Amino acid sequence: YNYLFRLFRKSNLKPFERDISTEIYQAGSTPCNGVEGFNCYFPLQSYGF
Amino acid sequence: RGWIFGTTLDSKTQSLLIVNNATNVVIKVCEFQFCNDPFLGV
Ligand SMILES: *[C@@H]1O[C@H](CO)[C@@H](O)[C@H](O)[C@H]1NC(C)=O
Image (tube, each protein chain N blue to C red):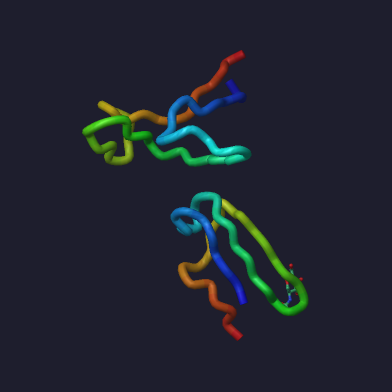
């Protein structure tokens, strides 16, 4: 699980953009209040090879 | 003598810092703590 990827963002990366940001992605009407929930997702995932 | 650049400038995320100290030019992008106004206290 030590190898990871981003699955969601506001918009696609520019050439050689290197964004570490770990803040909850808001994908709709509800605010995220600093936690995962409805319309509110943590942006990173693991491959688990 | 210097500049901060970034999005939030919060001393938490990735953010460019440039400082001239006369002996050197020092550049950082650090995901690290700095002052909210890091003036050179001569
Ligand atoms: C300027 O910064 C360097 C480290 O990059 C340091 O070694 C040097 O002593 C500094 N000069 C002054 C005048 O503080």
